[PDB]
Image (cartoon, rainbow, N blue to C red):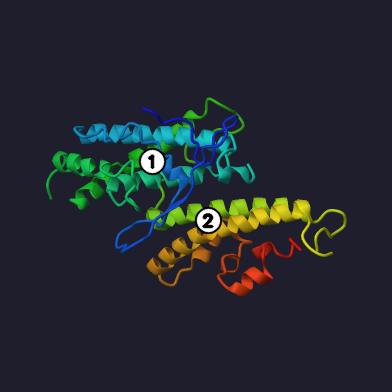
Amino acid sequence: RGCQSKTYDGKIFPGKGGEKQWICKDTIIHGDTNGACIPPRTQNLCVGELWDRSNIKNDTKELLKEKIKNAIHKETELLYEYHDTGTAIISKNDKNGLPKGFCHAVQRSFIDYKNMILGTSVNIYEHIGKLQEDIKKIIEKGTPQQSTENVNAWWKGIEREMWDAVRCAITKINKKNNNSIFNGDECGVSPPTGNDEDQSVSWFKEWGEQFCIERLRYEQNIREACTINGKNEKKGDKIQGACKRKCEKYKKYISEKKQEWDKQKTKYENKYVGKSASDLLKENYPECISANFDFIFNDNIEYKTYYPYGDYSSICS
């Protein structure tokens, strides 16, 4: 049942809206994994074979494995379409001849599958949930007794194969264009690892890439509306028409993103002592280089007065 074209950042043209939004949950004690804000992509994860209610209550680990593989293959195929058509927010920016943001999206969904199966899934997500309980039962009955350790070992034992589903799907795309010859290793010869394993970090990094890309889109729109003629617009007396409109859209945007930033920044910096949320985003995404997060999301009252449009207050005046 299902696993259709993605819609998490809006439907693919001629499709209208249907976009999903980041869902932030109050993070209590976090000793193992978690994650503060759930990505729209994660909410659109192709589960189908696994769930819709669990559909693996009485399956064997071998059949569980084939379903996971099928889900991963389809997810990769669907994400390719979503970024290729330039519908995903992170694909809009610029563009092997892989669509912009596609590899990052696939890596993130792979990590989401891993965490959903290991039971170490950040915020107990509605659709999945009880799915993890049945996984543990299937594994416990299907493997030699030495419970969370057995599921972990099982995943490690099949991880290479699951990643090959991604590589295989990438090569299967070689039925479309001859602009590039995909060998399947474009998104990495091995699955994501390191800090990317921690779903909390993966989600925050995704939030940051999207945020920075949208910020640049607002900047371009602002520049086109506030800087023609020779220089001025709404410098003069106050902010005029088109320039004010674009600047106001940005102010509104930052206002909405502030809550998401605070929660993720706090969770990340408290778990990774010494490391800064700003560095994490700037070291990973080119789009975040020009973003001064501390300035953009400053809580001072003097800030909203002196800089009504945040970091773009000078272009907006």
Tell me which amino acid carries mark 2: Gly
Q: Residues within 10 Å of mark 1 (few under 14, many from 20)?
A: many
Horizontal arrangement in the rendering, residue 101 relative to residue 147 (left or right):
right
- Residue drawn 45% across and 61% down? 264
Instruction: Tell me: residue 94, above or below residue 208.
Output: above
Q: Quadrant of the N terminus?
A: top left
Which residue in the structure is indicated by mark 1?
Answer: 163
Observer-nearest of 7 and 233: 233
Instruction: Tell me: residue 26, above or below residue 146.
Output: below
Observer-nearest of 173 and 289: 289
Which residue in the structure is indicated by mark 2?
Answer: 208
Q: Secondary structure at mark 2?
A: helix
Horizontal arrangement in the rendering, residue 216 relative to residue 207 (left or right):
right
Horizontal arrangement in the rendering, residue 286 relative to residue 224 (left or right):
left
| Viewer can see residue 172 | yes
Q: Compare marks 1 and 2 and give the one earlier in the sequence.
A: 1
Observer-nearest of 243 and 264: 243
Q: Give the Cα distance between marks 1 and 2.
A: 25 Å
Tell me which amino acid carries mark 1: Trp
| Res 85 → quadrant | top right
| Res 234 → quadrant | bottom right
Instruction: Tell me: residue 77, above or below residue 218.
Output: above
Q: Position of residue 166 (x, y in %)?
A: 42, 37
Q: Position of residue 211 (x, y in %)?
A: 56, 54
Q: Position of residue 97 (x, y in %)?
A: 59, 38
Horizontal arrangement in the rendering, residue 317 relative to residue 115 (left or right):
right
Figure label count: 2
